[PDB]
Image (cartoon, coloured by chain):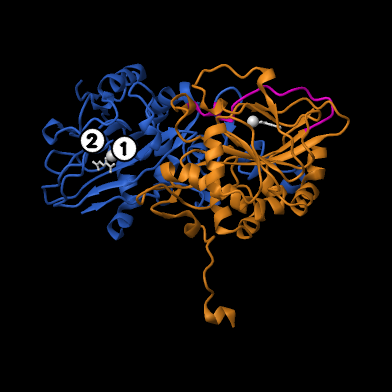
Chain colours: A orange, B blue
Amino acid sequence: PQLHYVPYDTPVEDVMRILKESGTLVIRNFLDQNTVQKVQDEVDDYVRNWKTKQPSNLSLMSKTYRCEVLNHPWMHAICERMFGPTYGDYWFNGGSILHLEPGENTQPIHQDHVFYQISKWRRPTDPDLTINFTMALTEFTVENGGTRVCPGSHLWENGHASPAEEDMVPVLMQPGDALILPGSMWHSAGANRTSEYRRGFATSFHPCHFTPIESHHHLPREMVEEMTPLVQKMLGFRTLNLHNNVKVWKAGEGNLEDATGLKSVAAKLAAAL
Amino acid sequence: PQLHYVPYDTPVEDVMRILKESGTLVIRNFLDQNTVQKVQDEVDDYVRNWKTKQPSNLSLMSKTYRCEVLNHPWMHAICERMFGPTYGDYWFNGGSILHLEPGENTQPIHQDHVFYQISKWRRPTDPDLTINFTMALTEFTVENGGTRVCPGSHLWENGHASPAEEDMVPVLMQPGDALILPGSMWHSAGANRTSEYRRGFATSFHPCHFTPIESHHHLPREMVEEMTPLVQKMLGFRTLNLHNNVKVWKAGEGNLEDATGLKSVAAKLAAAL
Ligand SMILES: O=C(O)CNC(=O)C(=O)O
Ligand SMILES: O=C(O)CNC(=O)C(=O)O
Ligand SMILES: [Fe+2]
Ligand SMILES: [Fe+2]
């Protein structure tokens, strides 16, 4: 296994194969510079007012996050293939700013899926329990604490010791590149030994039958109405389909998004006039 | 293993032991006749307007369900012990009326947990994935299709064939008795060979890290404010605690019920005056 950096236009099949073999990869130019700047602009004061800062609530705080980032075609292409065959639908798990102040120490090496009790029942050949997209806002370098990964460690059995620090491979990214982190990949933020902060931000998704880290039930109705149907489902506003007519997150026997009136209906002609 | 019928005042420890050994049991007088009648009164028109009827949405349709039944001390005593050590919090999964018209045929024998993909990873010695309380509204008899169980079948390995029909043990209940059905117990409704309908209703609960069959996000704010804090958590209005400060269903980094203003605050003295 190896850390691969692939162009945006790499076929989805090839990315899935790299994930299976190596457990992680970087997609270059995952976001353009416009999206990097709009996200920075929308979150920068929230981060400063928040040596590690990880504020979440990103769909509430960032219109670009809820209207654009969560529709990202690479996220959905990967998630449909990782979760679809086994579970059906998937939805958003959590997502935060990943901000390292100058002087921050190395983060403990971990698997993101450790907080699922069912990770103890899972085998390394089973689908992952969650998947994270870690997108660079600043450059990620060795010296500023860019995330480090241990390619192949997603295949280790449960209870395997963490990789040694010397086994960790730093991920070198320009603003807008993204690191893909299945829940089984061992990884960690590095130490920021520079005088400038290192910042990225994440999305993550997991099967529809697992409860997200973050609810979005507190978001204003008006924000929910500006989301696409897909993002409404990602953020907990729609009923979820398993397989063969099995649904969870139902309003009684019907769909939540019908019961809440979230789905658009046509006005009566008289009301329009 | 045997089907046991126990009095309401049976110690919780003894009920948990019976569940472990036999996989099911009946608690007599689980509800009093007042609660049976109030639930019937609140749902009867909804059932008739709905040879098997299983309408859900019970917290919306029944004040007694959301204000009284979901606070039932036996449900919480069992669920805390079944789910607490492994997962921390639990919450409501689904609950419907269980109505058999005269002439209905025997229901396929099943385990309730089959729709969880992770039931394939679980072992019979692991905690159940869900637990159901099936409460009699009418009497449950052999002839009217009272639920049947196969004591001990919760310990069978995954992929074991269903019990034979001749192995099924009918559950004979008076109005207000309750049958306890862990997700691993094989069971089914029987045929209603009488001229009168047979009706019960259910609650069910499962670990906080799994997505409920039913959302309650469509319920009016005013109904949510009349629930106890416990029932608010049961029905998806509160952040959920795993272990060692891990939470899911958070509003950002804080609690959902704070972000929505669901938790009562004291008015300003001037506003009160
Ligand atoms: O910030 C980083 O580079 C990596 N962070 C994490 O893996 C995390 O917080 O789970
Ligand atoms: O209605 C009954 O007696 C039993 N019903 C079920 O087990 C069910 O619908 O899952
Ligand atoms: Fe991580
Ligand atoms: Fe059942």
Q: Residue at x 71, y 43 (%)?
A: A177
Residue B228 numbered tag: none
Tell me which secondary structure the magenta stretch mostly adopts: loop
Local secondary structure at mark 2: strand
Which quarter of the picture shows residue A45?
Answer: top right
In this rendering, position of residue B147 left or right of residue B273: left
Residue B211 in sight:
yes
Do labels 1 and 2 touch, CB within 8 Å?
Answer: yes
Q: x and y percent of residue B171 in the render?
A: 19, 33
> Looking at the rendering, in which quadrant would you find the N terminus of chain B?
top left
- In this picture, which residue range is highlighted in magenta? A100-117
Q: Secondary structure at mark 1?
A: helix
Q: Nearer the viewer, residue B254 or B36?
A: B254
The residue depicted at 29 percent of the width and 38 percent of the height is B135
Residue B66 is situated, as x and y percent measured from the top left of the image, at 44, 43
Label 2 belongs to which residue?
B187
User: How far apart, in angstroms, are the residues tagged by discs 1 and 2?
Assistant: 8 Å
- Asked if disc 1 is less than 8 Å from ligand 4, the answer is yes
The residue labelled by disc 1 is B112
